[PDB]
Length: 270
Image 1 (spheres, one colour):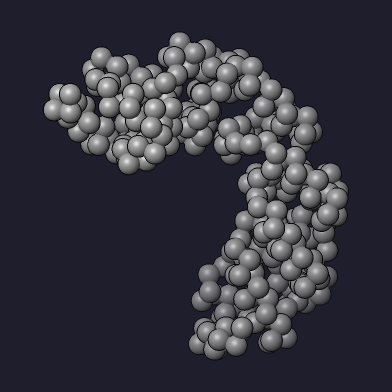
Image 2: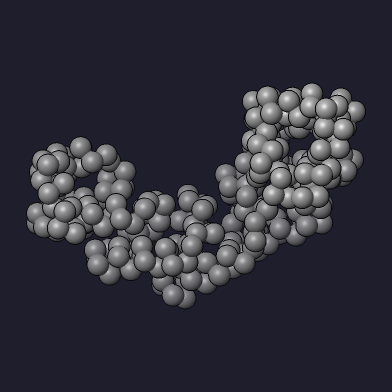
């Protein structure tokens, strides 16, 4: 059987499928080992093309979704029709399935319940709720627990108001599932060590999408230089987005007003 399967396996490899990943899932791997490309696999690939997975995206999709050959094609079609009934366009669904390859493995009822959860939990407009999951489609496929927990962390532990949270998460949807320890450490540093008020953090939520060491290195250097001026009502104001976004060379010259060599020297005292 190995010899007769070789041409199918070769085809999957040429597509960029990583069989070593699929091999971690023994029943799926044993099914694939027994599938023929023309008879069993091709009709699945043609469906994926129709929903918008391009040929050069199939390898990554099939490597992630080791379960796709175990779903009934009729059910996959029904789930796509459900998404369309919810006003997700063809372009939306193509992006959602590529970025969240398990999406069509969820039943109609589960997809409906998951969309309803995000509507109820975040309280966004219908439209902004669709925009949110089009932007981060894995919200629909992952555990919902970190979402519930992080909503309570932002409000009850970090002190943001409900409207502030909506503002931040629509811009940075990954905030909804971010590691709680990392969110807390970033908040404590930016709010308490840098003394930045909630309403300013709300305006620049990308600080929750920045690795904290970078925020810290830059704040400590500016502090060392007497240039850590984060209040827009005073001169030499440095905004949080400048601080987290501009590359080292420009941060040094334009913001810290110091050489990169001196920044490097400072970082060695940390």
